[PDB]
Image (tube, coloured by chain):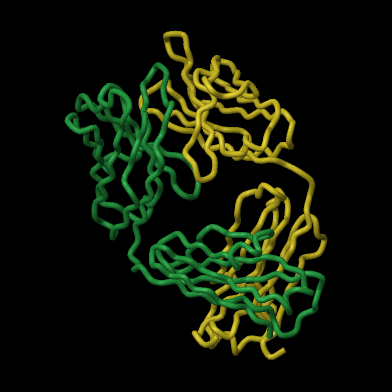
């Protein structure tokens, strides 16, 4: 099977800037008739993919002119002139030369802006979960940029990794930031034997890791 | 032109899953119909295409013997017999029309969810996220409301009828041992929380669970 190589994996560009993404084929995908058949797909979060470029030398009927495609016999490049709020999504390559047909690797594309300071917030369990018999410690990290950030859990100064749930969302629209949730679930009996629980965050915009700790017996 | 698919399907591992593809607005049995597999994590992998007129089928070298297509000429519907299914194939499936060497892929489907697991449909468990007893009162304060142990997706965790909608963050679903755990948070001024009554509400339509819960300081 002829594999696709899309470069780069993620290309954050600002509104109005020209962005170019390359899509190389592992073998020659030029057909003997004299035409190369490749498809470009644009998928939005929660919706089915759309069409923008088929038969690269041509344009799709219904897409505006801000998109363009070019390339040599093997190397292909998709170019966008002015990135709009609608152009958010994921790109995909599709070769149509040999049997069978295959997709690409998927190119992540969003917008880019200045750096942001992360907002860290820790939440101990409540009395209801203690009545139930558990201990859920939550650690939110909202409104940070870029995605280069690490979260660590410390129990009485010891690194803890079992029971860590790390989740993140996409880039929001109104503020263009990132969010990350770190959940730690333990038993109530273990909650009464340890003393200090700590959520620590390391981000580029902070020389020192943001520390949020709390003690059981205070 | 219009495409219809089957609803969500759950089943124990090892059995078969039958999904249907309905097509209208064109000559249904004149050109290829191909299906696409999208894992909820990343990437797009295809599964195969069929020609509803003749018994011409092909498969990708990686998914050989995993699915077997079937076409119907009398009724405009395509089926797929699924082989022994494992927990590594739980993903979303799309259907689309395709015609090689010419204009192709101008429409899609809507999406079909296949959730294969061994758990049982359990009602959610709502718990508040109250801050610690000793905490420094800043200009603003963050909130939290958690839901653990529910199946299947989705669930809607909101604040008081949309009163607190600015600065909310809903994370994707991530498993811990066998079920889900999702939290909601929002930032409110610290001069309002000791005064205004706030209650996090949780709605689970698959189990008809409408549960509100008030968060009170310590």
Q: Residue at x 38, y 52 (%)?
A: B90
Horizontal arrangement in the rendering, residue B44 relative to residue A70 (left or right): left
* Image: A151 above or below A95: below
Quarter-of-image position of residue B49 = top left
Q: Residue at x 49, y 73 (%)?
A: B211
* Image: B109 above or below A129: above
The quadrant of the rendering that contains the N terminus of chain B is top left
* Image: A147 above or below A29: below
Query: Residue furthest toward the top?
Result: A33
**Nearer-the-camera pick, A46 or A37:** A46
In the picture, which chain is yellow? A
Q: Give x and y (percent) for residue B181.
A: 51, 67
Horizontal arrangement in the rendering, residue B118 relative to residue B146 (left or right): left
**Nearer-the-camera pick, B155 or A189:** B155
Q: Give x and y (percent) for residue A93.
A: 51, 30
The quadrant of the rendering that contains the C terminus of chain B is bottom right
Query: Residue furthest toward the left?
Result: B74
Can you see residue B178?
A: no
**Nearer-the-camera pick, B141 or B66:** B141
Total count of labels: 0
In the picture, which chain is green? B
Q: Give x and y (percent) for residue B19.
A: 28, 45
Q: Give x and y (percent) for residue B3.
A: 35, 35
Quarter-of-image position of residue B62 = top left
* Image: B95 above or below A125: above
**Nearer-the-camera pick, A162 or A87:** A87
Q: Residue at x 73, y 68 (%)?
A: B188
Can you see residue B27?
A: yes
Q: Residue at x 58, y 62 (%)?
A: A166
């Amino acid at each position: 099977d002829v594999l696709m190589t899309q470069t780069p994996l993620s290309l954050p560009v600002s509104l109005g800037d020209q962005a170019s993404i390359s899509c190389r084929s592992s073998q020659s995908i030029v057909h003997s008739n004299g035409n190369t058949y490749l498809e470009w797909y644009l998928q939005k979060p929660g919706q089915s993919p759309k069409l923008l470029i088929y038969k690269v030398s041509n344009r799709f009927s219904g897409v505006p002119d801000r998109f363009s495609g070019s390339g040599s016999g093997t190397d292909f490049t998709l170019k966008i002139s002015r990135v709009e709020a609608e152009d958010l999504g994921v790109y995909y390559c599709f070769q149509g030369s040999h049997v069978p047909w295959t997709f690409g690797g998927g190119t992540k594309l969003e917008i880019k802006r200045a750096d942001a300071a992360p907002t860290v917030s820790i939440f101990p369990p409540s009395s209801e979960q203690l009545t139930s018999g558990g201990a859920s410690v939550v650690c939110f990290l909202n409104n940070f940029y870029p995605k280069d950030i690490n979260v660590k859990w410390k129990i009485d100064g010891s690194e803890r990794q079992n029971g860590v749930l790390n989740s993140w969302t996409d880039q929001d629209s109104k503020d263009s930031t990132y969010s990350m949730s770190s959940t730690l679930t333990l038993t109530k009996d273990e909650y009464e034997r340890h003393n200090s629980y700590t959520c620590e965050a390391t981000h580029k915009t902070s020389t020192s890791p943001i520390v949020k700790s709390f003690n059981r017996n205070e | 032109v219009q495409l219809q698919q089957s609803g969500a399907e759950v089943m124990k591992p090892g059995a078969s899953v039958k999904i249907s593809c309905k097509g209208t607005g064109y000559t249904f049995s004149s050109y290829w119909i191909e299906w696409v597999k999208q894992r909820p994590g990343h990437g797009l992998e295809r599964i195969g295409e069929i020609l509803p007129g003749s018994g011409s089928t092909n498969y990708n070298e990686k998914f050989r013997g995993k699915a077997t297509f079937t076409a119907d000429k009398s009724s405009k519907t395509a089926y797929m017999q699924l082989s022994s299914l494992t927990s590594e194939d739980s993903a979303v499936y799309y259907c689309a029309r395709y015609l090689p060497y010419y204009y192709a892929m101008d429409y899609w489907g809507q999406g079909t969810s296949v959730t294969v697991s061994s758990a049982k449909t359990t009602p959610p468990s709502v718990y508040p996220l109250a801050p610690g007893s000793a905490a420094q009162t800043n200009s603003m304060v963050t909130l939290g409301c958690l839901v653990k142990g529910y199946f299947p997706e989705p669930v809607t965790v909101t604040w008081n009828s949309g009163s607190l909608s600015s600065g909310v963050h809903t994370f994707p679903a991530v498993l811990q041992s066998d079920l889900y755990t999702l939290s909601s948070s929002v930032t409110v001024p610290s001069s309002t929380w000791p005064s205004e009554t706030v209650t996090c509400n949780v709605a689970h339509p698959a189990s008809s669970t409408k549960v509100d819960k008030k968060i009170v300081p310590r």
